[PDB]
């Protein structure tokens, strides 16, 4: 149950720029090489969106309480409240507009690191359950491998 909950959002943010020359085209098949959450490492995935933006590592306390989410990959420029286009810096405090999971939307987040890269939204087949996780947000270009 907790697998789909950690990839529980389905709305694409406004003003998000689709990638001009992504390494992995939309509709292409990739392998996820990162361990953000259980069931993703080495999973079969399909690219459903590719965008040129700034990806941030963030730390925040969920709005519903419980343990602090430490160094979470990723929230993007377009998911930070009132951010506009100015790049956020390490240590900056912000309000998250992202709702990837329960307690994230409206949380006070600290910016841990930032990077301009291509970020991908992907469908993937969980390696632990075998269930199709839809439009998971997000994985950067360097966390994907060509199928």
Image: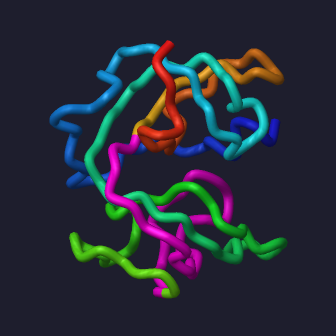
x and y, in percent, of residue 38 in the image: 78, 38
Span of residues in magenta: 92-119
x and y, in percent, of residue 40 in the image: 69, 32
Is 132 on the left or on the right of 56, as rendered? right
x and y, in percent, of residue 78 in the image: 33, 61
Residue 106 within the segment the image draws in magenta: yes
- State the image quarter where residue 72 is shown: bottom right
Q: Residue furthest left?
A: 20
x and y, in percent, of residue 3 in the image: 75, 37
Q: Which residue is pictured at 82% across the width and 36% down the height?
A: 1
Q: Which residue is pictured at 48% across the width and 78% down the height?
A: 95
Residue 128 within the segment the image draws in magenta: no
Q: Which residue is pictured at 39% across the width and 61% down the height?
A: 115
- State the image quarter where residue 131 is shown: top right
Q: How is the image coloured?
A: rainbow
Is 139 on the left or on the right of 34, as rendered? left
Camera-side residue: 20 or 107?
Answer: 20
Up the image or down, 131 lies above or below 85; here it is above
Camera-side residue: 13 or 20?
Answer: 20
Up the image or down, 95 lies above or below 39; here it is below
Is 102 on the left or on the right of 76, as rendered? right
What count of labels does the image hold? 0
């Amino acid at each position: 149950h907790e697998e789909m909950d950690h990839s529980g959002s389905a709305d694409v943010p406004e003003g998000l720029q689709e990638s001009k020359n992504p390494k992995y085209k939309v509709g292409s098949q990739v392998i996820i090489n990162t361990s953000h959450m259980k069931g993703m490492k080495g999973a079969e995935a399909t690219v459903t969106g590719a965008y040129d933006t700034t990806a941030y590592v963030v730390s925040y306390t969920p709005t519903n309480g419980g343990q602090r989410v430490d160094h979470h990959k990723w929230v993007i420029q377009e998911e930070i409240k009132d951010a506009g286009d100015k790049t956020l810096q390490p240590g900056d405090q912000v309000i998250l507009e992202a709702s990837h999971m329960k307690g994230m939307k409206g949380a006070t987040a600290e910016i841990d690191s930032a990077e301009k890269t291509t970020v991908y939204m992907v469908d993937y087949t969980s390696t632990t359950s075998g269930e199709k996780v839809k439009n998971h947000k997000w994985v950067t270009e360097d966390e994907l491998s060509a199928k």
